[PDB]
Every structure is written in structure tokens, then in C-alpha cells.
Length: 320
Image (cartoon, rainbow, N blue to C red; front, side):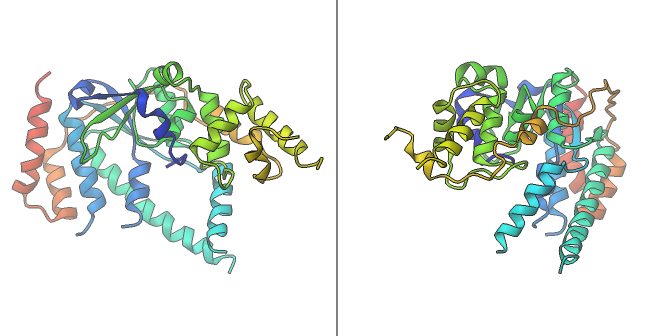
């Protein structure tokens, strides 16, 4: 999700840790990555995965806050419209394609929230981007960080990220921004400029521009904030207009969108819509009896089958 493979660049800034390290931490959990994965495709396997995942969290005495997406921002809605209409090649025919998609994500929102309530796990509906709201819970010190596999959080200014926390590999990667800012020399603004080139949810990139081509462009036009891309654009708009060899001749062959770099994109990552207010989050003891019913209704699980998974979690919670 987000950018094509920003994770590849950050590999070397990631300490591996044991789930046991996360014990006691308040952590934002991004559920929107799960919702999206499950939207494509045994009955209710999405809920089963959520069920297991919740057990892992509570078993390791993590106090998670689930964050669901609010309204999609303008740039996102626009870039999804261009890109879906670039893949194909009536006006109310796609309006029905978005209405069925909106009920399916609508049920899945409700089903997940039910399960969370039952496990005493608090959730919030972010205003805009969950990732951004998770990022601001991070910055306000309301969480000790975010559990997500979406590299986008970094662009919304996340400090602490736990990645691959739900994997068949089962090595939890812990990243802090501070460590990749010092060890790979990669700041927030550089990561944003990379969005502009590699392409993101807020902007399509430049077609033939990979991790390597992109980094070359930022090293070729050193600057602060958006300056590097502004100089790149100026030079390119000037090495187009006037028809004498130079090292980064590769760039002359690239063809960018007219308004690039549109500062609206940087603005959306830098000053996103979020709830800065200090919230009162609570954590309930899981309603064993109501989870048994849920598992009966959704998985067709007898009590015992539910109990097999649930008890180890509960007994594991009743030590400090």
C-alpha cells in the first residue's frame, strides 16, 4: 500500500524484536490494510484472520487502538479516478461499482467493530487517512507507536512502526524514523519527494522511474523541502524548450505531467486532516460468552472450539 517499495530503502534501519518486547505498549493498529486485502476474497475468512490477529495482540498484553479510514481526501479520489480509467483504456455505471464496494466495506467495518467491542478493544473513525491519525496518536505520545505494514505512515510523520507483526515469517521488525534519518540519511521531506517520483495514493509518479532512478534525481538536485523537485522541474522544462553533453541525460527522456511538482501533494502529507485532541481510550475485559456466540454465528464454532483459542489469551492477560 502507499508507495511502490519505500520499505526496500529502510530495510537496514529495522531492528528485529520479539512480540514479548511490545508487552504493555499502547499501539495504534491500522485495520484499513486488512479491509482492502479481504475485499477481493470457507465462509468469513476475513473475520477469522481478524479473530486470530486480535488473540495475538491481547496474548502479548498490547493495548491496541484500531483506526478505520474516514473520508478519502481530494488528491486520493482524483488519482484513483485517473488510474482506474488508464487501466481500462455509462457515467452512472461506475457509481454502482462504488455503491456495491461501499456496502461490502460497510459490512466489514461493522463486523470487525463488533469483534473489537467484544474483545474490549477501542477503535476510532479517523477524519481522513487512518495512517495519518495513527501517526498523530504517535506524535502526541497517546501511543508508543503504530502496528502497520503501510510505508505511507512515514510520510504522515510516524516515529515508531512495528511491521510484519502478523506473518508466517514471525520476525517483528521495529523501525524508528530517528534511526533511518541518521543511518540512511532519509528525512520526512526526502520520503515525500520520493512519493512525487515513485507514485503514491495522492499522485501518479513518472512511468519508468524506479527506486534507483528516483534517488538519482534527488541526489542530482540537492535542496531543502520541495526545492529539489522544483529545480529538477525547472531544469527539465529548460532542457526541453531549447534544442553540450551531461551525466544525467537519462532525465531529458522522461515526460512529466504539466503542473509537476504540484505542491498540493506535499501539503496533503505534511498538513493532513487529523484529530490532535487528547482522547480517553478504555480497554474492556473480553466478553467470553459474547465471543462464543460471534464465533458460532460467523465460523460455526461449538463453545469448546472458541474456548481452545480464547482461554490461553485470557489466562495470559491475568498476569502483569
